[PDB]
Amino acid sequence: SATEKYYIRDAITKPAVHHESYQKLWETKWKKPCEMGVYPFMFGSIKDFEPVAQEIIKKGLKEPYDWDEYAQMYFPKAEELAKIAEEAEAAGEKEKASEYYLRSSAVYRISRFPTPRSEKQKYAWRKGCEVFYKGAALMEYPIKEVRIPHKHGIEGEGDVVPVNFLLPPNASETSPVPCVLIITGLDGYRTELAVWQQGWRSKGVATVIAEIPGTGDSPALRQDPTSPDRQWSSVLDWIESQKAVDSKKIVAWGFSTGGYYALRMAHTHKDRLLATISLGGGAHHMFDREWLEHANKLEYPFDLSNTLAYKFGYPDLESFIEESSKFSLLNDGTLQKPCTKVLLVNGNDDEIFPIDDMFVSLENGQPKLARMVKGKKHMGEPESFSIILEWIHKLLGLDGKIKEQLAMIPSR
Ligand SMILES: Oc1cc(O)c2ccccc2c1
């Protein structure tokens, strides 16, 4: 029975209120993080989103969403902010231009949540990236796009791995810096996790941000479990070519769905990584029929299981569930292989990926570092971020000033 299968027990049968309407999503889940300027509203302002939310609520939009109808609600605000940014840049107001380009990028971003599954959402992805990089270019320490040649790609794969790159000042072959490789999630891509880069730069750490297969601009085959392996071979070849980066001090940090990829590459690329971190990742039970047949109605803001199916290149959930077992790090033998240093962190009560997958990760191969966060759901925030930064600071011998670093994340 499904109600007795997983750690959270009968919690999987209780539908979350935010699935009733956008009004319930805004009031019970999204308004607070929007006000606080945190995921999924990094770089964003409540001043931009509240008026849009008011118009969506008046229209009474709800599941099942028409994603073209949904996306269009955000475009007037996104365009308004982009025009304010363009005027500021022309006047030499660098700081103001940067702010409004990034505020524009945030509005485009939410219009194509949870993943671009319509023409207007695919449009919003391209528009979001354009204004993001315009804003990124006008930062004091500019974040740049690098189109890494996908030299390890095979037939049907893209020619480049587009990544964010930030190198601290005074980094050189003579004085090389560690690199945190951030692996993004199912809905948050390189334009979202970018919020972490200035913090790392301030601690003398380079950052590269790359998307998982079937998200953002990942060139990887969606249905091929080995496609991430090729992508990381291309990305790590490129990092090793950057002599200002110490390629003996590459730390991979996977966020949410990215955690699966961070855990996987700890095995596939052991000798090229100092450590990997899975924050709210899965490994095995995340691919279960039982888990996936319940997850659409739980803590995820939209349809988690359907979004996962799309990201893995399946036309519907049933087709994904029929083949999903082949992605398991247990089933495909990954977890039996030696791994580099691994840190697993998650909330016990996660209703996006089960904590049961931390157990599977700890039940196979070499010992791994773990922190469980009791009484917290997906990502075990906020303590998870302090746990991970404390550990990375010790690993890389940084200043250990993690409060100062975390204080830079909220948008203001
Ligand atoms: O900064 C963040 C915080 C989160 O809770 C995230 C969750 C999923 C993906 C990216 C995130 C980034």
Image: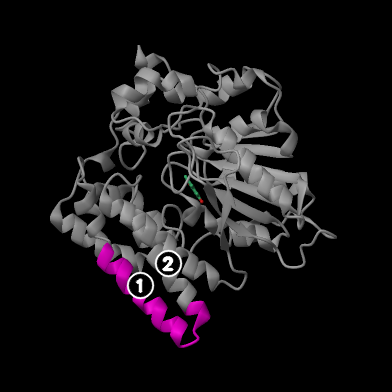
Number of dots carrying numbers: 2
Amino acid type assigned to the residue bearing label 1 in the image: Leu
- For mark 1, does the 10 Å Cα neighbourhood hold few (<14), some (14 to 19), or many (20 or more) residues? many
Magenta highlight on residue 283: no
Q: Nearer the viewer, mark 2 or mark 1?
A: 2
Q: Position of residue 44 (x, y in %)?
A: 41, 63
Residue 147 versus residue 15: which sits nearer the camera? 147
Prevalent SS, magenta region: helix
The structure's colour scheme is one colour
Give the quarter of the figure containing the N terminus: top left
The residue positioned 43% from the left and 64% from the top of the image is 130
Magenta stretch, residue numbers = 75-96
Q: In which quarter of the view is residue 359 placed?
A: top right
Kindly state the secondary structure of the residue where label 1 is placed.
helix
Q: Position of residue 61 (x, y in %)?
A: 18, 50
Instruction: Say the numbered circle drawn on residue 308.
Output: none
When the figure is inspected, residue 365 is found, relative to residue 104, above or below; the finding is above
Q: Earlier in the sequence, mark 2 or mark 1?
A: 1
The residue positioned 42% from the left and 15% from the top of the image is 5
Magenta highlight on residue 85: yes
In the picture of the structure, the residue carrying the numbered disc 2 is: 131
Q: Are marks 2 and 1 in contact (CB under 8 Å)?
A: yes
In the picture of the structure, the residue carrying the numbered disc 1 is: 81
- For mark 2, does the 10 Å Cα neighbourhood hold few (<14), some (14 to 19), or many (20 or more) residues? many
Residue 234 versus residue 319: which sits nearer the camera? 234
Between the C-alphas of marks 2 and 1, the distance is 10 Å
Residue that extends furthest to the bottom in the rendered view of this protein: 91
Quick check: can you spot residue 245?
yes
Q: Position of residue 286 (x, y in %)?
A: 45, 26
